[PDB]
Image: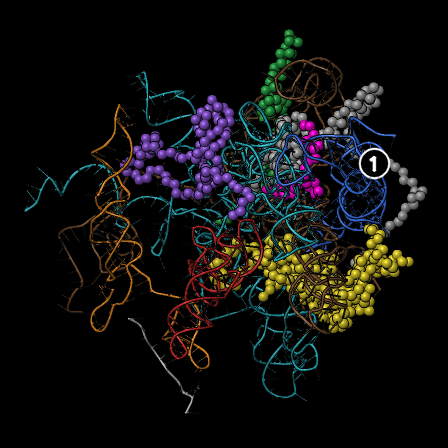
Chain colours: B green, C yellow, D purple, E brown, F orange, G cyan, H blue, I red
Amino acid sequence: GKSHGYRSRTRYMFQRDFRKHGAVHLSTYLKVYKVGDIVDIKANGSIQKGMPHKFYQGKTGVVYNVTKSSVGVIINKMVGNRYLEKRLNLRVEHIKHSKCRQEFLERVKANAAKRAEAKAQGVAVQLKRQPAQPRESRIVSTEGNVPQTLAPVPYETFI
Amino acid sequence: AKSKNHTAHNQTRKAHRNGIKKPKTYKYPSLKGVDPKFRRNHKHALHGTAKALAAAKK
Amino acid sequence: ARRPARCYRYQKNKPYPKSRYNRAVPDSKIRIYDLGKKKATVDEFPLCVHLVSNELEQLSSEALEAARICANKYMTTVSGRDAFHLRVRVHPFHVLRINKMLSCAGADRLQQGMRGAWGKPHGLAARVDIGQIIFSVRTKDSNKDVVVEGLRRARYKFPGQQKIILSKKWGFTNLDRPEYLKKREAGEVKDDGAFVKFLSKKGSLENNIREFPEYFAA
Amino acid sequence: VNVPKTRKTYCKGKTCRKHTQHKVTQYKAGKASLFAQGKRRYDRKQSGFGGQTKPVFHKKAKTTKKVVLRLECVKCKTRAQLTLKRCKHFELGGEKKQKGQAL
RNA sequence: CGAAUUUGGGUAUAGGGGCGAAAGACUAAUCGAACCAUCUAGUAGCUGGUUCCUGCCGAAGUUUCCCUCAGGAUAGCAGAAGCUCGUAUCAGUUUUAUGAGGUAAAGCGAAUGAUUAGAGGUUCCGGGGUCGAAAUGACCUUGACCUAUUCUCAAACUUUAAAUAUGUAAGAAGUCCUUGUUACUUAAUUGAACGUGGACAUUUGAAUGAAGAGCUUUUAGUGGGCCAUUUUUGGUAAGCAGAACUGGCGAUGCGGGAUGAACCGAACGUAGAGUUAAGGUGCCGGAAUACACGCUCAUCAGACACCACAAAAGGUGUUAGUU
RNA sequence: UGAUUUCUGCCCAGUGCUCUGAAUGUCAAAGUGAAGAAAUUCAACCAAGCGCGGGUAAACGGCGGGAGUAACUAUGACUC
RNA sequence: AAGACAUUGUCAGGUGGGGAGUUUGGCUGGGGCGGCACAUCUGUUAAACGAUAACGCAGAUGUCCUAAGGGGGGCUCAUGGAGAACAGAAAUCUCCAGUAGAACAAAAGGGUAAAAGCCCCCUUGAUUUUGAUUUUCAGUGUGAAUACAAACCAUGAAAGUGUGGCCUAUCGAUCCUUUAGUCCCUCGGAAUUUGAGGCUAGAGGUGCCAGAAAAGUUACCACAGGGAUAACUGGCUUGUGGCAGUCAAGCGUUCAUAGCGACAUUGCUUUUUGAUUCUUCGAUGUCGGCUCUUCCUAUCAUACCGAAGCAGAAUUCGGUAAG
RNA sequence: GGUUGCGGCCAUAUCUACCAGAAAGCACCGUUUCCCGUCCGAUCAACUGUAGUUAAGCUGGUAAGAGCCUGACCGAGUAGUGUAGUGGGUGACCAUACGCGAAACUCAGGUGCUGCAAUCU
RNA sequence: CGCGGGGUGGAGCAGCCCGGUAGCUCGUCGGGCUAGGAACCCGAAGGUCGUCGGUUCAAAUCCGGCCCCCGCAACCA
RNA sequence: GACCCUUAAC
């Protein structure tokens, strides 16, 4: 018959790594998670307790509960036509802080800092990010860079 | 007589008719599922702030 | 008998090797893959002619054996057994299955139709790509017509279209002809059993001087 | 499986409320009393004409039962029950497993 | 065809009963259980039918459970009724940032497993001999002890590792103070969580759009699906069986493919004019027997995707090209 | 079963049918046996039946394998 | 004559297809047989989130364990190399080398090296109470169980760890019975002691595993239906069947090709049979023969001809040819 | 800059074979009365700062070293692939358009970096 | 091409209340009986159990493959 | 009690 256990189809997902087996380096147990922190979920296959389900590998959530060894994570999961709020009790080895979250907080401070400098003089700092713009006009000098003319090559075997 | 066994055909289309809206977010989530030791202490701390605030704006 | 090759010409299924999940497969029809003066040296045979495929298909082990025997027999009878070195560069690793339908009587009464139709192994084939060499012949430059003709004769044993293409490498080496001579004037290339070893600029210099002595001795 | 005859576990007897020693015995299902309401109602239903009036199970599939250990606290006589996993062989007589002995 | 004969009338046997030299025969054209009335409009997940118009919206053949598989319940899809604001905290999309993945490809002188050939020595049982155990004996053969190569591979192998698809974030519920509270926590006003006062509307912290957000109740039908392209499993294959994503048909007319559910184009109130799409323009047939360069002559030419098939192999037939 | 004629072989292990009665075999109502209060378990050459033993096939029915062996072969009277 | 026996009446065991009533799964390339794809678990199919089918492939489950659970400590495994007095290929003993090539109950895949492996010590956290969560999912139940809270514990110097088994499987409703849980509540005219009934948590089991109590036959048959589904034709396919081709190792006395032709390989046909289930189950009359017409050509005969291992006769091969 | 103790990332750190190491620092170390487990004071436990041992550990250097890491218009815009056509091809497959884009290979470079507290001529 | 059993000396059977590293009968051989055959008596030999791979508590009985002896089902249109 | 057999080979 068919087989759908808890860890079915997890052969490579929960595989440890190449030359990264054994004990976990302790910085993962030194990281601190507060309620509201944005965390990623990458299950560590060596630690079998507090393991996320395979659905939650690669999912990013928000901490809502902090216990002795684990954090409660809220994750939005798509069930049918709507997202359901799921609550994961995950041990710290299976989570890490989202790096994009930390980068945006630096932008928040950088935006506030830039506003403070501009407010001293009113130079329209324009904190808002912009998409890559079409190139402006430029002049290409040819001195020392004479154009080298190219043609399609003939066909040949090379075997 | 054999029938069709399973297909997810048309299921994504059905789920998008009035569909995939995110769950509505609130200020003050429910404190169910959070540690009772924190919950019990939070109750006392919130009580004191209401008493402390009431004294200030008497 | 054997079912026609038309039934297995093309690459329809995933590679199905003999394995612990197969564990019972017919033997391959071709067991010899090196013919002619196989013990030769790379300086002996400077010319290489390739029989290459222009189709992504499958060749049965039986067709490989037929082409090999045909190509070998012509070269031996025309130019001598040890005037060439032919190496078939494909090995039949994909097993072909057959759903054995009954040619008995009362067939449909207990045939079960397409129920449980997963077939049993009945043959082996090599899965080749466009531009992949099937046959290679090492020989002398004065034997070009003979070994081209042998591959022309062997083309009739394969399905699909094949090209007889001359290699610009010396023998079975990876180096072009005039790139081989400069590497050979220097003591950079040493004769192995039938292939050759190469002087690398890397590794321990103590080993690189113990071998390739002519390279360092002026 | 092999289960000892004594077992220090939590006792809820309003007098222990802690870990104390217990005597360990297998559970026996007890004799089905006549004059239990179900039997009184059943005997009434089976009386007279009609045949068998209730189902009788036949499609038995388990080759095993669940062993229930009854535990009597040696302090306060408060009895307790717990059920073990399915096992085809159960023994309370604890013949300890010896590791490094020849056969 | 003189009898176990044929036969009239009377009589007897009545329906789970009779009668049967036996055929389930016969019992009033009824018999493997007669006929009549009633219960009885018996039940039916099954077949058939189901009666006016227009307008607006508009599906499903999928999930889970069921003696469930021609049925139900449930969720989904749909309708209706609405309810809570003067710029909707959103999106089948991109960008930026940040994750997750083991497929394609690649690899196998990288592990596992396969797999083709040649390159040193060595009586650690056995195949043999110059000489006869002649002592580790001036030889090769599985190598019973050795590394450098070499050809070819993997759905249930892999160091590496895309594309597409996918999670999150891009702020007013956000950010910057010796606590303000606590019974939690800390060695400790240490923190944690939640706060009071302070500083931030045309940029409120990417883009594009937004057709009003958000929310509730209730209920119909459906729960046989099928077909492109692409991925893909079983099968020699199938107008075969089975999956993935999407788009379609079902439920859909219209222009084109002569013709055709699905292909191409385009989706439809009633009309008019002008442009087009796809497809066409010798005649049928609206539209160049137009322009331009070649090629082909078939004693089965060829002639337009899906699509209504043709192959290997050959030809100083013809044309171009390479050495 | 199916005139006559000539015959009707072997098997009672099984299923029946039938005949029998030591019951440290089974065993229903009723009846008989502890103590305060009673509604409330037992035992019993416990009735038959069933079990135990015998008969019965013109009851239903059933009625075997393997290997070797004769001085040409083949076969197998014979032999395990 | 017979006798308080029989008989009769009531109750209680036995017997009782003579009779009655009822039942006698499901999936399924038709059904049956077979199997279990019916409750599950591993890898793959599976197309790098998740999901994902087939009677796809390769396997496994209904168990097992007072340790194989818990804690702590100490120590490294498989395997090769190096000696010995009967000791050898396998008894030890000692050094080396050794990323795990071992072991960890089982299937498989992950995971684990001062350990998760092996040995030793102490233990029962495989315990209480009842909530939150994850997976299947309707976000119901069941099974597993992830993180806590309030107790009691075990272990350890301690930090800590432990709510069974390194992780992914290893299982069970209503009703009834039974057990455990301070005679807690009720037995309703008032009491006391038995009995009974309640409340909470287990067990006894439904494997068709969200869980009926269940043997056949019908060739005497019936009904509602089904072309959702078999037994003809027809259609797709062409494996198998049949018929051709290319290559040319060989045969043919010393010669491939007169005639053949292996190893291969390309096809054609639908005069075989499978495969499928599209049409037809409110019915398309089925085998064969007889009869009769036409068509095809893959030519047996007859016309003309080419070739030969055609010296004549007779053949053989081939061409145009179905008149 | 050496070293020790505690660490972080966890080979640019590992592996092989040689060469070197002043002061500081394991221990050459020495011992078994005492706490401490056994066949073994070898490990482990405890006790001392001795002849003065750098022999080993450790650190550094070397090696056209193995491995590992970084990079590259090196291979290679190649393989692969998203989207498109009433493109080609009997088919098998392929070419083209708008995008994304590897891995081997080759060539170079690199021999841990670094936090806290001490200590050192 | 489905479902089941079985394979141990030349031959027939013992490991099937999970284990004596293989035993019991016939056959064969040796001796003795008898004036040789037979019959009889006394002794002996014979198979690492069809093959290969799995737990390593004497494991191969019990597990999974191939071969062999066979047996039943092979129907309704 | 049991007890079968006996040259083709002058």
Q: Residues within 10 Å of mark 1 (few under 14, many from 20)?
A: few
User: In the drawing, does residue E163 fall left or right of residue C2?
Assistant: right
Label 1, on which residue? A135
Q: Does the magenta run of residues contain D102?
A: no
Amino acid at pointer 1: Arg
- Report whether D76 appears left or right of C212: left
Depicted B54 relative to depicted G208: above or below:
above
Q: Nearer the viewer, residue D38 or E112?
A: E112
**Tag 1 subunit:** A
Q: Position of residue A50 (x, y in %)?
A: 61, 33
**Percent of width and height locating residue C88:** 72, 62
Residue at position x 74%, y 27% from top? A105
* Residue C27: quarter of image: bottom right
Closer to the camera, E159 or I56? I56
- Return the x and y of residue A8 as percentages of the image width and height: 59, 42
**Dot 1: element:** loop
* One can see residue A59 in this view: no
Most extreme residue toward the top, as rendered?
B58
Residue range highlighted in magenta: A8-33
Q: Which is more toward the observer, E319 or H4?
A: H4
